[PDB]
Length: 316
Ligand SMILES: NC(=O)c1ccc[n+]([C@@H]2O[C@H](COP(=O)([O-])OP(=O)(O)OC[C@H]3O[C@@H](n4cnc5c(N)ncnc54)[C@H](OP(=O)(O)O)[C@@H]3O)[C@@H](O)[C@H]2O)c1
Ligand SMILES: O=C1NC(=O)[C@@]2(CCOc3ccc(F)cc32)N1
Image (cartoon, rainbow, N blue to C red; front, side, top):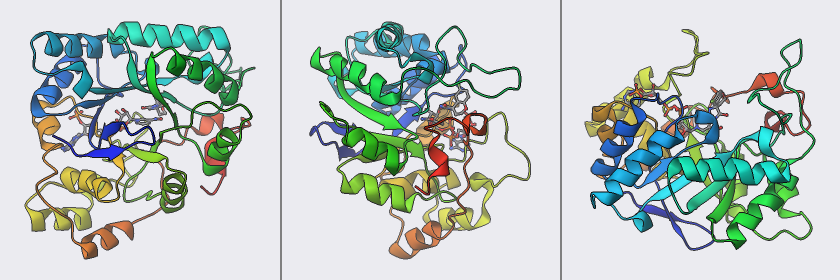
């Protein structure tokens, strides 16, 4: 039902997907069921979201009830940076694929470029709260991930929260077998990513926009923070088209050929978020929205800003 962005592999990635970060156990299964019924085919998942098993339950049931075929679903997951060491890449992936109850993933992403210390903690810190870096790097991780593609377990690899310098480092890696098909990064009218998007597309790499609604449910939201959903200029453009702000925020990416993955566990909103192929933002409206860029990140991960491959010190 969503249109598709063509990947460098010629696979078709549905341009709208369901986000699952912060979707609680006990709600996410129904959210995915509702989404599939509404015509979503792309679901965005991650090991670190700690809810992939419920996502897997929903997909499995919808497939068995013949609501959807596996071939028409596009499931993305991510390798968390505590798992960059070779045996850990496979073990992390295997837990993800098992939880999701799939025989293959459509895309597996490096979740963040900066490595974290391996062990039991997802967010390893020292006695000052600073992230502890790891031994293996994302280049090491990538090599282990390429094996998954060779074995038919993953159709395509991608990256997330990478700057152009880091994509360069990957594309230049000696013996590189597979190129990233997407870079999943924060993107919305307050962080328009013009240079990064330009760079990615010029390398034949798609962009997946995360937190497109401004992630209002992120734990660290402060009342004074920018709030896209409440932005009167966005709402004004919405009103013109008799749509909601969320729908304009989602449509914005579609018109830049950028994949977008709004999260909701509210059934009415899940449905609302995909009613975005029946209107069109004018050229003037796109330019106005583009002009709202504030270089504001809802997802900064400042706790890890000291690590070698922290991505957000670069200009883009
Ligand atoms: N790669 C990464 O590092 C990374 C980082 C962040 C996010 N992501 C991915 O991107 C997805 C989306 O980003 P996000 O979860 O940060 O936030 P988001 O999708 O920008 O916003 C989610 C919030 O918006 C609300 N909402 C959804 N639809 C709405 C609507 N139509 N009207 C009003 N409110 C609405 C949701 O409430 P309800 O759910 O209560 O309806 C939820 O609180 C994530 O879930 C995750 O899959 C990836
Ligand atoms: O979808 C997300 N991927 C992430 O790395 C992030 C952004 C930064 O904050 C956190 C914290 C916990 C978590 F599970 C996830 C996250 N949200």
